[PDB]
Image (cartoon, coloured by chain):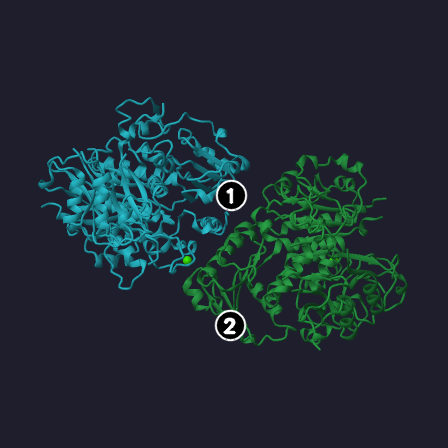
Chain colours: A green, B cyan
Amino acid sequence: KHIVVCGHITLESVSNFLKDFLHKDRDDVNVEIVFLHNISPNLELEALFKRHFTQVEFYQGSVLNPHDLARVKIESADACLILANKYCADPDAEDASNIMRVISIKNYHPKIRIITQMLQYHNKAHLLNIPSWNWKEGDDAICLAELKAGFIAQSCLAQGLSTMLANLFSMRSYIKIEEDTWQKYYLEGVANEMYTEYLSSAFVGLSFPTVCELCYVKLKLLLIAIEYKKRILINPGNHVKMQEGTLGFFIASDAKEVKRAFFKRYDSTGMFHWCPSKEIEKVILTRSEASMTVLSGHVVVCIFGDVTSALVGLRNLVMPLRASNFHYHELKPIVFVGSLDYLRREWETLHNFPKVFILPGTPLSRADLRAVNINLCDMCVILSANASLQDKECILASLNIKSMQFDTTGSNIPIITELVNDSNVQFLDQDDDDDPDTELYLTQPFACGTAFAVSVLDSLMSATYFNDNILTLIRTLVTGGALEALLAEENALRGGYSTPQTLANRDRCRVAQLALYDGPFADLGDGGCYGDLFCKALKTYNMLCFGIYRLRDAPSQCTKRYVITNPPYEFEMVPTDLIFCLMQF
Amino acid sequence: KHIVVCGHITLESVSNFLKDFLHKDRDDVNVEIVFLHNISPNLELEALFKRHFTQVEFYQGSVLNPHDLARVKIESADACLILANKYCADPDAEDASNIMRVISIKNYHPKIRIITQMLQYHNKAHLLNIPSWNWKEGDDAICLAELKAGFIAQSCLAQGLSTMLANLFSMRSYIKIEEDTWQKYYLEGVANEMYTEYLSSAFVGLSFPTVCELCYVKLKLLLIAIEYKKRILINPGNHVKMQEGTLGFFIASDAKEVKRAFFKRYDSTGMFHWCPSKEIEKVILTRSEASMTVLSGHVVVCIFGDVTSALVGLRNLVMPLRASNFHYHELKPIVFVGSLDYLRREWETLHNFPKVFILPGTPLSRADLRAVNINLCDMCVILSANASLQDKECILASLNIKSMQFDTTGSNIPIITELVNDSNVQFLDQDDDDDPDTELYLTQPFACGTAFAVSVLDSLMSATYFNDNILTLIRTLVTGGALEALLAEENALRGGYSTPQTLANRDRCRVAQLALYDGPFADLGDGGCYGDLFCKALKTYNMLCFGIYRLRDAPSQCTKRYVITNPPYEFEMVPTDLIFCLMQF
Ligand SMILES: [Ca+2]
Ligand SMILES: [Ca+2]
């Protein structure tokens, strides 16, 4: 078996792809990776590669040349992966180019699995027009815009989820730092990767909750979702019972570890909160009108950009924040602080969502910022519209906010800065240890969920090759809902009257972050074991706890909290801890 | 005798020119071709050429240099041909440049025959301002914009006509594929080229129809038009009788084969349907206003482009669709799906034509597409406004439409994609055999009239040198009407009250495609010979049948039909066949 990787192939992209391919995964001996570029050979740089991995071959040529496709033997190949220029000049033009490859690869041999990256959502739709494109077979398209947005959105609900859900996906091994610092605990979690496995015949008929306990208690495998016979269910309630050989998504250290588990108020779907399309000027707040309202528990997304910028795809940020699993009362209002000229062009996708607001002005003016009462928000998202040196602004905005005093203090505000250049992470937190060479996942600002780069998702490519499900899990988890045709035929979203079959869909779980201090399970804090809590939390409310969001201190000063994924049954808690979890509805 | 070729002379252009010059034509020994470029000599590449053809000489220099013109001896030369940069950066600038050459060549020696290519129609007019320019002598200008448009227009009336009328013009020989596939039948037709010949004294006084039968039955030469003594008549009625030595246009395999034939509701002209100039906003349909009307039997021309694009010259697409040979009832309404900003600038030429509509929006949104009820149209033209890699859009649009389901199916819609790069043909039909090297005329999508490139017309250059008439035939045939001064003085077109002399001009024949199933001559189908049908069809209704538009199957599935030009008197029909023909009025 062999695969064909093509599209934007750079030294950096190849090296990154190879790392993620061959780590803890069960078998790597099987697949030969054949890269196909059209750039200058650079035989020397390639020469060494071939020596380290005997599974790697380089050929130049186009994906649009029937001879070259035959030369690389695309027809026989297990799958073909099309890498995109994430940091492209014109995003629309890039997708346009990539779509053509898909068309071509399908033209040569239709029965091929194609994994492809997409920069803009709206373009992802086009892929369905291609005859040979099988959404139901292996063909899948990783939309970078929609996922980047969703990950940041999921952080508004539970701060730090973005980086927790990212480290979980990138294949990485255990490090075991000897000295006592947060690094130790953070990395002990990082060591995770999320694997797919079939449930043992033993579990058949049991309730998911009881199965989940057995897996965690008897095996130390944190189970999060089943694949009912098809639709997938994340943390089902106690009623769900196992159907012969069910497929389960586990979060364990190594791939071999998981083997052991074998012994009109709504959208047409009723998934998202629909609202009558509103005219943009009805939403625009004056600086005063905004300062008048004391907003809190809201999301302040402040975007830089002018009329001639790439569309960030704000649709995908608000959508998961408007899922039906939250009550209208619970919904967080969203305030965009940007240029009106920029906003309006994107606006057309958002008019349907409720509690959306625009305050024209720059994220660098405190006047605009004080007006929207940042001190009070649950999350402040800082985005840079697309030369990457010009993201200097985001750092400035971030630093600005940290140095305010509301009368609370600026440094204690939930911020999440989207960075374009992983190197720039050094700057946003100014007490951390800095080095340009140090990987992003290891930096403090990332560990805490203060920062997030498009870079992080590149790992998904290989990961979604191995398990189709993985990609459909995350997309489902991150965006709220998923179907595509209603969404595809029109980019504008249809809203309908609720049927008892639609009001039924509200039953999906939801991400939340909880405290031990006010907790019903509070008694466990102040020294109790996480293992003892987890089970209690599960059986009593059907809650899944998969992470502690601890302060970076074990004297006390800072508020910054870092992420610990899937801690062991014997893990000492503290009163200050917070719990990442999936609650029922 | 010798000729001077100048202007845009590339390796590709030269090789193409030489192929079309020296094939089946009666005598090639007579003419020496002298190329005059101004690019870097590249003596080596040229060296070989001179060795294959002893009729070819290369000289560098300008056409604007009196010395160089004398050196190439332009004054003695039979004719001078000016090739243009079809795939130019700025079309207007290219014509500007070419016109200057014409001016210069005329300045040096006025009594010269000049054949020249023009990219935009509006510029073609300017050539009349040049004193030495003789529209009545040999001087003729092949306007690429007007012909490309007309060929596509002619396909709306009879699908596949574009490629039938193209293969007919490019000098090509018989191939005789042994195996039974559509290629065989298609190529047996392709082997045609349309030649000019004088009628034998024998035919004098007979009716065209009876002459036509004799030519087809006794000689196997399909005759299509006479040149009455001057004006030319395509398929005249039975009344027209031969005047001594008449000139006739025949469609035969070889040039020597033809030798054997020797043994206010209207425009000022009353040629085209005039309508009071309408204000653009009166024509613009909302998406709703359009979805409201169930349009069918119409043409959906959907153009990509913004305000800063080259003008496609839509005038020339609608004009042949608005000829007076059709009743107002019979007229096909035209819907443009594009950017309003782009359209309005072109619009000013169209306000005069009736049943014209604009639906602002992109050909990639199904909303806009479903609104205009594509399922129902007789033809859907896909155009790309002018870097040629950016025609990727046309393929996308084409694929989009094929994958829709109206509730009919998307794949069964009459589409014609204008391609800029002959190579890209591979992509539009995804069941055909693909190879970049394979010539365009041989590709399935072209064989069927699904695709059409500006490339195809390059053959005309040499062909119109040999017979002035040929060019005036096609232009007359393709655009409906032809005179130039009324059209030239103002680009806007004058409409007048009809006189009985103008209402007389409506008598021109018309292209149409007919079925055997519903046919009056239906009985001949299901096994009968085409020869037996042809004559019957001619004598009974004065119809000329010149082609079968057969399905590509001889089990059944596909709807795609390919073109067979001038089939023999002994040709087996089928019920599924269609007939290309010229009907009377
Ligand atoms: Ca720092
Ligand atoms: Ca093809």
Look at label 1 and name its amino acid.
Arg
Residue A503 can be seen, yes or no:
yes
Element type at marker 1? helix
Instruction: Tell me the crowding category of disc 2: few under 14, some 14 to 19, or many 20 or more residues within 10 angstroms, Cα based.
Output: few
Is residue A139 found left or right of B429 in the rendered image? Answer: right
Q: Picture coordinates of residue B167 (x, y %)?
A: 28, 50
Q: Picture coordinates of residue B175 (x, y %)?
A: 25, 59
Give the label on residue A47, or none: 2
Is residue B272 found left or right of B468 in the rendered image? Answer: right
Q: Nearer the viewer, residue B509 or A113?
A: B509
Look at label 2 and name its amino acid.
Ala
Residue drawn at (46%, 65%) of the image: A60
Q: Picture coordinates of residue B462 (x, y %)?
A: 24, 47
Circle 2 marks a residue in which chain?
A
Q: Nearer the viewer, residue A181 or B411?
A: B411
Circle 1 marks a residue in which chain?
B
Is residue A512 found left or right of B284 in the rendered image? Answer: right
Q: Are marks 1 and 2 on the same chain?
A: no
Element type at marker 2? helix
Image quadrant in which the C terminus of chain B is located: top left
Q: CA distance from mark 1 to mark 2?
A: 54 Å
Please report contact status of discs 1 and 2: CB closer than 8 Å, yes or no. no
Q: Quadrant of ligand 2?
A: bottom left
Q: In the picture shown, does residue B367 fall above or below A438?
A: above
Q: Picture coordinates of residue B261 (x, y %)?
A: 13, 46
Q: Nearer the viewer, residue B452 or B286?
A: B286
Is residue B325 found left or right of B391 in the rendered image? Answer: left
Q: Nearer the viewer, residue B92 or A520?
A: A520
Q: In the picture shown, does residue A374 fall above or below B495?
A: below
Q: Name the image quarter holding residue A28.
A: bottom right
Give the label on residue B370, or none: 1
Residue B71 can be seen, yes or no:
no
